[PDB]
Amino acid sequence: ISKKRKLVADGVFYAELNEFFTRELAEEGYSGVEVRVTPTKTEVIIRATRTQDVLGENGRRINELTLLVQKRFKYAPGTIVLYAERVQDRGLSAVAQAESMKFKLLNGLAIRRAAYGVVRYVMESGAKGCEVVVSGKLRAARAKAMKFADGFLIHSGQPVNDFIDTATRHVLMRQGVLGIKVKIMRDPAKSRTGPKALPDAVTIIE
Amino acid sequence: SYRGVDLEKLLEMSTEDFVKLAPARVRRRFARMKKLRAAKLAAPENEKPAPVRTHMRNMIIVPEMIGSVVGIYNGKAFNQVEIRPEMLGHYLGEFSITYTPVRH
Amino acid sequence: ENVWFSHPRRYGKGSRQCRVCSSHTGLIRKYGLNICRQCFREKANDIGFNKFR
Amino acid sequence: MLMPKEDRNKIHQYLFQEGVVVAKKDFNQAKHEEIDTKNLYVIKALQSLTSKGYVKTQFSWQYYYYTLTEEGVEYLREYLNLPEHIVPGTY
Amino acid sequence: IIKIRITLTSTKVKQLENVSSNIVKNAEQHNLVKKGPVRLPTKVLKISTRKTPNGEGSKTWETYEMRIHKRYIDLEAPVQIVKRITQITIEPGVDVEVVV
Amino acid sequence: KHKKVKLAVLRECSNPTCGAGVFLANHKDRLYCGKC
RNA sequence: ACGGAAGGGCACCACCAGGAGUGGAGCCUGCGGCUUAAUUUGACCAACACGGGGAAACUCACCAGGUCCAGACACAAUAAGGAUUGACAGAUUGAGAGCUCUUUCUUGAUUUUGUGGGUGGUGGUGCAUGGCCGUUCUUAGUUGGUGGAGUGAUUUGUCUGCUUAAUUGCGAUAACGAACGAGACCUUAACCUACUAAAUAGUGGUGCUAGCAUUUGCUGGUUAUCCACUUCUUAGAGGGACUAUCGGUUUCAAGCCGAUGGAAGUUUGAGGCAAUAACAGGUCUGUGAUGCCCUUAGACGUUCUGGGCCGCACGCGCGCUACACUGACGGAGCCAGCGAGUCUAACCUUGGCCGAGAGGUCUUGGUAAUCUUGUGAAACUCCGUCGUGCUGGGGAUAGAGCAUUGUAAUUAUUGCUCUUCAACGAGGAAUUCCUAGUAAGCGCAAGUCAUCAGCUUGCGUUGAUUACGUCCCUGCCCUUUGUACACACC
Ligand SMILES: [Mg+2]
Ligand SMILES: [Mg+2]
Ligand SMILES: [Mg+2]
Ligand SMILES: [Mg+2]
Ligand SMILES: [Mg+2]
Ligand SMILES: [Mg+2]
Ligand SMILES: [Mg+2]
Ligand SMILES: [Mg+2]
Ligand SMILES: [Mg+2]
Ligand SMILES: [Mg+2]
Ligand SMILES: [Mg+2]
Ligand SMILES: [Zn+2]
Ligand SMILES: [Zn+2]
């Protein structure tokens, strides 16, 4: 296979795995996968807020997930290894927060209460700004959209790719779908990778 | 008569032989409803065979179906036409019009 | 019955589909993506396609 | 569905020998990639007993993922007449 | 001493350069002879698509790019410290092919 | 509209997978079993 | 919010000065209408080469027909002398379909029959929705906290004046201090005789070495034929521009205008990203996004055959080709850039041979800075024929034949050959796009794609005229002002 098609198919496989784990490990707080390719084996590092439900009793769940990925992607047994490591900071993951808010709305919680809970948790988890948009038939009506923001939020430029986390979920209520959008601006100061400030931020020494 | 072959020879010329004296499309297609005789012979003489219906609008007229009455489908309402030696080399669908003339 | 239950689908728009949504229209067949144009827009960042210019 | 007994047993034995079944959503594929059986047969034997339980199905880009449950292990033990020590491969 | 060529391909230029520099430094610290890291022109896998999921509105188009960067370094090295220099490069996102 | 007339309580050929339960049917000159 | 109110600023989706046109012709294509069994359907600046919508089958949603259940599953009405499944041949059928029948064999607790309950649906609802796009709006706009004003809605901050592309800044000041937007940013296109490094890029000289010339020179081939180098090329790290310097002019600065230097002085050029509020804007026909409704075995599920989406008194939108000599034709000259390409396999194809052509055939290289490919592109240039005539302009329509793709080219897929040679003599009222490597002309790659570009997305080649403004038209921003408008001047 050519390099163009190989890297494109690697991206496509990453997207496949990401959506599969998004659908499978929703209740386990899945937050994102990473595919490392080693000459002997491929490793898939899952980040899920609950790294015990993904594992399962004596690893039952993680082993059956490895079996599923092997059987789907035609992998010789042993050549792929799922590792559910950790989400270092739940409050900074837009995907995790969106999933949590979807779960809260599904099992029953007022839209404003759930959204402000997410916003408050994100802000107290060190984020420099959060925004939750809930769109749809909040109470059976003309399908308004409610925004709940705290902190500040640049949108947009290159800094949004740099440090902005956005996630969109469909909550399936008994009256249509509600759309959840979560935007988190992490603090550029504690970046630990990439630029440590905004491009227009200037700090002088004396 | 076809292109250099009289009707008598035509009526005895097998499809394979006839193809060689036929234009590019038909012979390429041949290089790539046999119940017709069951109405050609199993019918009173001095009369026409019973119609034989088919959906195959892409059947090329060979000098083997000459004389037979074919009901060609054009999407509905099989249309009966009598295969004549002038039809040779044409598609069955050229004689069962698929649409209604507009007539504004 | 089971003999006449499938006609050729070796080519044309009916042979292939989006690997995500199984739609026949708007497919992206470049680099072997085989994804609908809308699904490709949805998951372009996951594959590694980004907007620069 | 109306499927052969031996084909249903082939699917059942692959299920409670590996733990998971991954079947493409193609109800006309002649053979299943893993099992020497019709893909339609696999898919429908699971749209079967996954409805009584015993399995969980996830769709995920035109590719059903079936995973056994506890009731699944028990029921398939009874079905295949297996002693209560042969855990699924995933165990 | 066998002659091998290492081809590195990745979309992430920073880690591709991390791997290429690790390889160069490992070859220098093992005192090998290497032809410098050749950077073949980056392939911009662009794709043009219509922004709208339907046919309405101003016809606005959208170009997505996958920049794939490629590098090859060929040198001469024995078996043990060629296996070690191909097993030191397990950086994620970079694909590495060693050809003899 | 397959009805399958009840056919209340009641030879052999080649292809020995036909295991002596493949009795032929007789309308006239019918030498073909159920399997074929 | 609006004004046929005022003031200030601004925009080739406005105009002025102009260029190219479009509107007139033929054809291509989309829309309406008509026709039809069906001519599926959405959409009416911000619908109409749009749905990536270039539909032979498929796609497909429509029409004439024919199959199958892919009707899970707790449950009760069928089963251990058969609940069920399938079928040769013939009728039957388009069909070599066990659809159904003639009718007797095969299989065997998987179904079948009814209830309940599911499942699918390109069925409806985009005025129930998510998401995504478009638009308002390509402008410069938007918002808390605390303080000030008002009973209040609300207001100030967010501003007179200058300035800027900019709510950009100078500054002013019942505000102060902030947030988003703008900018900054990111990508790309310019330069760098500087760094690193290159038989996947190239250059010189040695080998070998054909030509010409013969005092050693010109141009050449030498892809395992050496050595050195990185000017060309590539890509990493960086540099470089900050309107720098000098004048002029600004209220008082912010800035602006000249010249010089510079690779580049309009945000350096082009983009990507892009706020707050909205629209009953489009999409349920992208979605295994989805609520409700409808349907669910004679199906609106699904599949198969055939047809249709293209059908033609006619109106409209995007376009292609032209009307000729600044040209057509024939030779010859022989110059790009962006890209794509096949390992479970038929993709990009060099070269040889055959063929007038299209094309065929035998090989070859390429999973690709390696080969196709220097993509030997077209316009263009030179030399000739034509000679101003519906002409050797134009190539519509049509006949005959040869090929290719495809299971299948009939309602012509396309290509090729010969023949036929229509309108069109520069296009009314109207109307579009555009200010520099731009307009225009020119082709090429990619997307769709088995085949099919007159389409689109990009790319390069040749390369103007005009202007450097204004608010007249059409609009936009701010302020003041009037309002009997708020569904907001439709
Ligand atoms: Mg910006
Ligand atoms: Mg004018
Ligand atoms: Mg024109
Ligand atoms: Mg349907
Ligand atoms: Mg709407
Ligand atoms: Mg106040
Ligand atoms: Mg105000
Ligand atoms: Mg509407
Ligand atoms: Mg159409
Ligand atoms: Mg198109
Ligand atoms: Mg009025
Ligand atoms: Zn799709
Ligand atoms: Zn038998």
Image: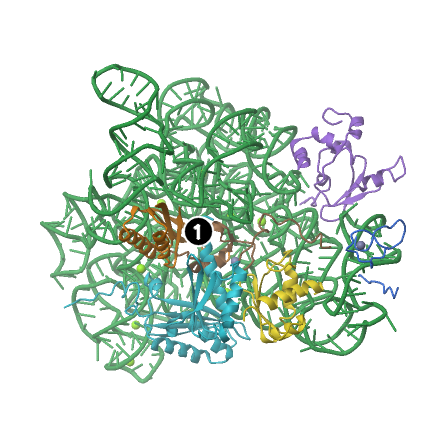
Chain colours: A cyan, B purple, C brown, D yellow, E orange, F blue, G green
Left or right: residue E94 compared with residue G96: left
Residue C42 in sight in this render:
no
Residue B76 in sight in this render:
yes
Q: Quadrant of ligand 7?
A: bottom left
Question: Looking at the image, is C45 positioned above or below residue G77?
Answer: above
Residue D59 found in image quarter: bottom right
Question: Looking at the image, is G420 positioned above or below residue G50?
Answer: above
Chain of the residue that carries numbered disc 1 in the rendered image: E
**Is the residue at mark 1 in contact range of ligand 12, meaning its CB lies under 8 Å from it?**
no
Q: Amino acid at mark 1?
A: Ile
10 Å crowding of disc 1: few (<14), some (14-19), many (20+): some
Left or right: residue B56 compared with residue A177: right
Left or right: residue E82 compared with residue G258: right
Q: Please name the residue that numbered disc 1 is placed on.
A: E47
Where does the image place residue G416, in percent across and percent down from the top left?
Answer: 55, 30
In this orientation, which residue lies closer to the viewer: G237 or E75?
E75
Q: Quadrant of the C terminus of chain A?
A: bottom left
In this orientation, which residue lies closer to the viewer: D91 or E9?
D91
Q: Residue at x 67, y 65 (%)?
A: D9
Q: How many marks?
A: 1
Where does the image place residue G6, in percent across and percent down from the top left?
Answer: 29, 61
Question: Looking at the image, is G421 positioned above or below residue A172?
Answer: above
Where does the image place residue G415, in percent across and percent down from the top left?
Answer: 55, 33
Residue G156 found in image quarter: bottom left
Question: Looking at the image, is E20 positioned above or below residue G332?
Answer: below
